[PDB]
Length: 469
Length: 98
Length: 49
Image (cartoon, rainbow over all chains, first blue to last red; front, side):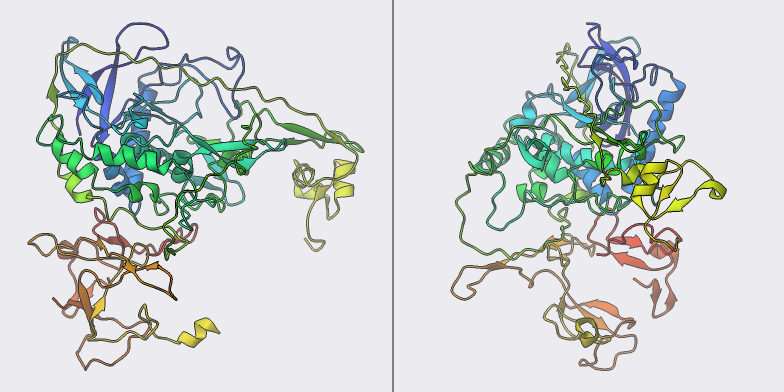
């Protein structure tokens, strides 16, 4: 597991200088750069015009050298935590053996440019996943691709922005959903970009919002978020990916042909033979059920909306295990109670959904084979098609390049604002049980009740569900 | 009633009680994938067992295949004979047949 | 895998562990994982193979 000084292929927030970063190999072909994502401008809370939801902003976080070697010890403790899980290192081995097709001899489409003591670029090192620090936004775990080769069949090198310092907590159980549950969710999604499957473009409706707009997810997002109903892969005459599987199959089964078209090593040709041995059935049926935790009993229902499901009170810090206290929590609705004020239920739900109203009407279906396929509603182990021991015996050598750097610009997301309604209700609602069931006083002065119309009116009494309790 | 009908036996896939000294295809229940020795050595590699194109009531169903890979007896700890049944808590020794 | 043989318990030098091993479908774990019997194994769902 080598460690290099890397002249990065991007520029630090419009500085137009060479970005020289210290990369570390944390798994084969998986590099960690324990610095923040310099390519989007690192701001403070007061500098952000329109902040995202649940989005703690803070500069100076991985500018220090001590706490950015604490960041490498959090990535190295995370990949050692995925390795200790069942089927965990066969995912990490699938990511290791998912080297994209070379653009030319050597690899000027997937390599990090290594530089000597002086900056003389002497060789480049093969990368698949670069595991960056947080961006401007600290909980904005993303999977930025290097190229648009991820929608091409070639496969693209992947930058994995990830922050282990922000976790979801099962508030009733006080079990912390670990950092690696979102890291396995993103290494899964890296496989669909390292194989050249264009599954990040089309967004499929998953959650109808209050104005009949849809919180839409990609087939990459849908498969990677573990088991979930409205399966992509619900065989009942395969329905999902209407006329899109034929594109994904042509992207996969053409890149398998061009495998000796450009020769790099005897090991680059040997990983590319082992890469297209994990069939396209295996990618679409990746289940990481043994690797993710069942901390949140519902994690396989929602489409990765764990922070909205559990609420923003559940987002905690790694080092403190308490609430983040600096996340902008901008609710969608402020439901206030009439007969006594200060009983607000801040409804943090989703907004600004896509207008996919004419989606289930214009639903094309693929030409079915007219065959009942005996399936089983549970997931499957699918790494039995993965040549997992044959990947681990291959280490790709460093490639002598001494060629100049091609820079690729990074243009971020433009998030919409969250307009907060201020609803004043004259009557108890289901939302006003959350306000009523919480209290901030001791046992001598708690005064519990089993009635909403007394806990909501008094602001001294607390709601409960059983008159004996 | 369904759990207590099965009693204290460990069953086949076909629903019949397991037996010592009986040739058993050992499969994985999720892929239905079966063991296989690496090229010349005695190390095992779990390989996938192909499905079956049947006709079920005149249709063209595609169902799980089970006859793949290595077979394993369950030899008991001092060998008796074949038709003894395996119960919950019965320790054995999986012997290769090939 | 009980961890014993017909000659008694198998040496952890020869075997690798000493107690029970579930037999999984994961190479690179060696198709074995330790049966966890600590006071944390029922905090989540067991995921039996």
